Structures are given as structure tokens and as C-alpha cells.
Image (cartoon, rainbow, N blue to C red):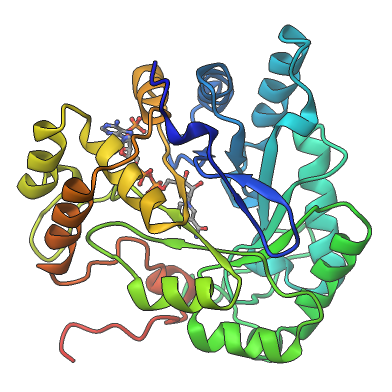
Length: 326
Ligand SMILES: NC(=O)c1ccc[n+]([C@@H]2O[C@H](COP(=O)([O-])OP(=O)(O)OC[C@H]3O[C@@H](n4cnc5c(N)ncnc54)[C@H](OP(=O)(O)O)[C@@H]3O)[C@@H](O)[C@H]2O)c1
């Protein structure tokens, strides 16, 4: 129990929608049936009012069941009290496919609408007749290059879903500054959120500015590092001695310190956990003192950026032209 927790703080998107600063990440590549339901229920009962989902996670049915059961067990809570965000995957970038994805997600979550609908990646890919990712002879995504660099159709579909009041806000994920310039050029409805990987080992400071200065709210996934360990040196963010020192001196958890850092920078954080204890503890986001904030920033600035989420080898498409040399 943290009375002064930032789990009550919200941000106001550029269309006036309120989004809780802390949201629960439901993606596990460990899914394992019943885990998503249990974790989502634990998060709702721990005080989370923000749920991050995605068609890619293939767990929206359990999330919807959890939401239904929670709302049924607590009459004082309404669906309007919850902020539900879901995303459309890469093979469904065709406008009809985008709409179908949103409808499928709504059916699974047992919701009439979502508060945030995000295009998961700026990469349109081909699909099979049964709405599965089409693999090529190399076993990698079959890229639709036309829809990939002139993504206006996709965004139009999103705008329509926005105007059909099926999504209260629409946005992008893993977008770049140049991609954002592209979309602004072509968009009628400016994206409200750009969900990206932000953490002390990948501060993403330049993109965080571009978004904030253009009325696009960043949303940080993998805010605790990730379920992944640094390849080039075998490092975990949550093992970093400086981060742990800052957390220990102020009698808070390392994850709490990282989440407070993120929220103090002014963006949303999406911690994920299957463990009940971590789900309870992650919601107790502290309002960092200036010393803790500056020291965490020191740790972040003393390092080579490290990006833990790069699916280059799966998509067969290098969005972020990052190489060993150079
Ligand atoms: N392209 C995208 O849009 C995108 C990509 C990736 C992720 N996301 C979103 O961001 C969310 C989180 O990103 P992530 O998957 O990299 O996970 P994360 O939030 O960065 O960190 C979670 C990892 O650290 C552990 N953990 C959680 N809380 C902890 C705590 N207090 N203390 C110690 N360990 C803790 C977790 O263990 P346990 O799981 O066992 O509890 C798990 O191993 C995802 O759920 C997803 O919603 C979006």
C-alpha cells in the first residue's frame, strides 16, 4: 500500500482522453493457459486501471474474462473506470483487416469499445486466407512494401474506427521520428500515443521529445528492461548496480525506482508480471526525489544504448538500421 502512489496520476492525450500513467502489460511469451486471467485479475484487484493488450499476444479472451469477473465482483467499478488498449498486428494492415482485427479483439475482450487502439508496428505484411502471418521461403514475414511505406490506408481505417466511436483514441507503436513526420503529413487525426521501448538502458530521449513536442504521448514498454538479457555483454537492467543503489538508498524496489523515473519523465509505463507479488508491488510507483531522478539519469547517460526488442530476424525487415559497427 502506497498512499502517495502515482497509480492515481493520469495524462491527457491530445484529444482530451485521460490515460492512467501506470498500465499493466499482459503480454507473455510464456502464456500459459490461465496465467493471463490470473495476472489480469490480480492487477485489477491491486489497483491497476490500465490494461495493455494486443492481438499478437493471443490472450485477449482470458483478459476479457478477467475484466468481466472483476467488474461483476465489484459493483462500484464500471467499465468506464478502466482504460483498455489493444493493437493490430502486421499482416492486418489492410483497412478491412484492421477493422476485422479490432472487432475480433472487442469480441475476445467482451467489450463494446477500446480506449486506445494502436498499430503495433509500422510494417505491413501479407497474410494467409485464415488470417495468419504468411511466411516466405526463408521463414520470415512477407513484407507488403506498398502498404509499408505509404501506410495512409491503414491509418484511414484507424481514423474510421476512431470516428465510429469503437476506439476512444488511436495511435502507433514502434514509430520513428521520420515515420511520425510521414503520418502527420498524411493524417487527419494525429496519433495520440506512440508506444515504444523506453528504459534506462534505452532512454530514447530524442524520440521522447519529438513525440512530446508534437502532442504525441510516449508510452514505454519494457520499462523494467525486459524478459531479455543484454546480448553483447550479458547484462540485466534490473541487475545494474547504480539503479539498485538509488533504489536501496530510498527504500524502494528497483522496479519501483525505474517506473518512477519513467513517469517523472512524463510518459506512460507498462510493467508486466505474472507473479502476484510483483503485480502488487509494481503499482506502488513513487514520486521520485530530484536526487534519485538525477542519479538514475546518470546511470542511463553513462551507457551505450541497448535495444532489447528488435525483431529484425523475424520480420525480415530492419526498421532500426542498427549494426555491430557504425
Ligand atoms: N511492440 C510493442 O508494442 C511492445 C513490445 C513489448 C512489450 N510491450 C508491452 O510492455 C509490457 C512489458 O514489456 P516487457 O515484456 O519487456 O516486460 P517488463 O515490464 O520490461 O519487465 C518484466 C520482466 O521483469 C520481471 N518483473 C516484473 N516486475 C518485477 C519486479 N518488481 N521485480 C523484479 N522483476 C520484475 C518480470 O518477471 P515475471 O513476468 O515472472 O513477473 C519479467 O521478467 C508488455 O507486457 C507489453 O504490453 C509492447
